[PDB]
Image: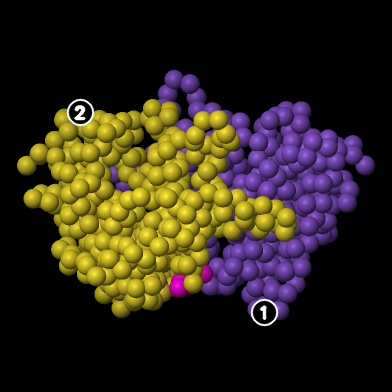
Chain colours: A yellow, B purple
Amino acid sequence: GGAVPGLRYRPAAPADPEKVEEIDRRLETWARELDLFSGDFAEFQFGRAVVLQHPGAADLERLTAAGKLLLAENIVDNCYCEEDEGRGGAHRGLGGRLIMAQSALDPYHGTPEHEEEWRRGVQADGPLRSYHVALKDYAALATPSQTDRFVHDIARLHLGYLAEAAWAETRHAPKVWEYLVMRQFNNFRPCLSIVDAIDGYELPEALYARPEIQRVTALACNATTIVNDLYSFTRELASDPDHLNLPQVVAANDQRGLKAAYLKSVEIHNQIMEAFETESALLAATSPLIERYLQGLADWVSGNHEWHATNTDRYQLPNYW
Amino acid sequence: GGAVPGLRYRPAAPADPEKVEEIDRRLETWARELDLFGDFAEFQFGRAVVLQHPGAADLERLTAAGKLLLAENIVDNCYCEEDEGRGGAHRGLGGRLIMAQSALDPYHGTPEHEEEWRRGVQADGPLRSYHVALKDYAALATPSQTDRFVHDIARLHLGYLAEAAWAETRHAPKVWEYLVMRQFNNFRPCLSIVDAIDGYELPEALYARPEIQRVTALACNATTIVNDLYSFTRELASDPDHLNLPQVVAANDQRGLKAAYLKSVEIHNQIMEAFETESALLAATSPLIERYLQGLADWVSGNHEWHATNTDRYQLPNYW
């Protein structure tokens, strides 16, 4: 009825409604105080998203912090990637707006005078304010190693944004593999970047940076990002048929119809999930800490899928079964 | 010898010619077997790394610094300075740079797509250079250190994309906004590797500290401004629309290029003074931090010497 038939996912327990509410309440107040906006905020379901995605969260403040980051991420995306610059003023382009967004996370250093102008520039736009203050509140809970991990994953995301915008401008028709390479960057990854911090512990960088740990993190991120493609397929087919998602790209390369492309896209997802779970299991047996991180990753993926599958307002499924 | 008058810099001991010469030989040899291609020594990659890494553990690690530097230049030249050839694939700067990032930061997915991606990276020189340079560096460095490098290259590519967006949209940045872009579009990926190249490791937990992040940026920003100062005259003739600190200062201040250039030197000096001053305080906290800060300083110093003595590529304006 609500989930994609044949899709591989672990059942997620339903989010504590009183937790969801308090989070959405807190996030609303925060957005207001930062002037980030006459509408119901609960409808975007940010509180529901983080409660599902971080079932092991150490406390409300850390859940709230995960929410602020997700909110900021969505604000920047919508205001810089989804909307063009208004006519008749200064014109910086995606590349220019994004580099200022990165600076909001990764602070500028120079002369006292130029730093002050930079600080004011960061205060002058809501999207930049949201990144700046979100990271600030997160950095108060997390280690510099953890914040630096998140900043790198945002850098990835922004490169992913710029790659997608480039292809759309140059009219590039990527093969499936190349689309998925872009989607490894243009990814939910920065939300999974924080699973240990939000749960109240740290996976040290020495472990995180290991190739085999980089691999399973990528596999989780790539799979759950594809989940977005699969649940957004129908709405995007109607609203902007030129937007790339995995089924469109499979269909454009394979030329065997959308239904075949969609079903195949589910199998690709399941294969990626399979490698995530098989390799996670092996890595989990080697270390209780690594184990705990992989469970955090798995739980994020699971909660994210549940959020998609039950958000019937924004996500509809095609009639392919 | 031939330095910007009034510029703040520290003496760099001359490069060992025997190493410079061997490094160049190795780099050209490496380049031919990866088929990335004339006198190759004219590029002076060998002299750059010898000057930039005076405390290098050995020739193998110097060579690794050369390969990274070489790969970074190849990508810059082929993707940022040159347009895609007509009549073939068109992916744009964004598209080419996302593949370049994947060359450093491996793709994971189904075995079929992973193999297609692998063939993709092998399919052109710029991606091959990144891929093999990093592989050679990772064999000598820790995974923390290679992650640090990948992050610095992500910064770089974002920096590229920012400078390109401005050229396209015809944006005239204020001086502060230009320098923000310049913190990303930066020599930083070469300063990223100074501990590993000298055969030790600054612990990431120390690297990640805000004060260490700050002094690192100060060093990187100063030495990158140094490139603006020495290339200014050349780019004046060849690419007047190419942004550098003097041009941006002059576009904003409107007091003429001479005034703007002298102001640019003063900005460099202030940022360099901050780096030295805050380095001095931080040094006493840890022998590893001290060694790292000296690596930064020696890189900045050698990079300045490299520019100041590359008579052929860089000239100075007649402002003194």
Three-letter amino acid code at disc 2? Gln
Position of B168 relative to A246 (above/below): above
Residue B93 in sight here: no
What are the residue bounds of the magenta stretch?
A: A141-145
CB-based contact (under 8 Å), mark 1 and mark 2: no
Q: Is residue A144 magenta?
A: yes
| Numbered badge on residue B17 | none
The quadrant in which residue A251 appears is top left
Query: Where residue A286 appears, x then y in whole percent?
Result: 30, 75
Residue A69 lies left or right of residue B279; in this view the side is left
Instruction: Please state the chain letter of the residue tagged with numbered disc 1 in the rendered image.
Output: B
Query: Where residue B25 appears, x then y in whole percent?
Result: 65, 46
Residue A186 lies left or right of residue A103; in this view the side is left
Disc 1 target residue: B285
Q: Give the residue displayed 16% in from the left and 30% down from the top.
A: A257
Three-letter amino acid code at disc 1? Thr
Disc 2 target residue: A255
Q: In which quadrant of the rendered image does the C terminus of chain A lie?
A: top left
Q: Give the residue displayed 45% in from the left and 73% down from the top.
A: A141
Say what secondary structure mark 2 lies in.
loop
Q: Give the residue displayed 30% in from the left and 54% down from the top.
A: A40
Residue A321 lies left or right of residue A168; in this view the side is left
Instruction: Please state the chain letter of the residue tagged with numbered disc 2 in the rendered image.
Output: A
* Inter-mark Cα distance, 1 to 2: 63 Å
Q: Residues within 10 Å of mark 2 (few under 14, many from 20)?
A: few
- Specify the principal SS of the magenta part: loop
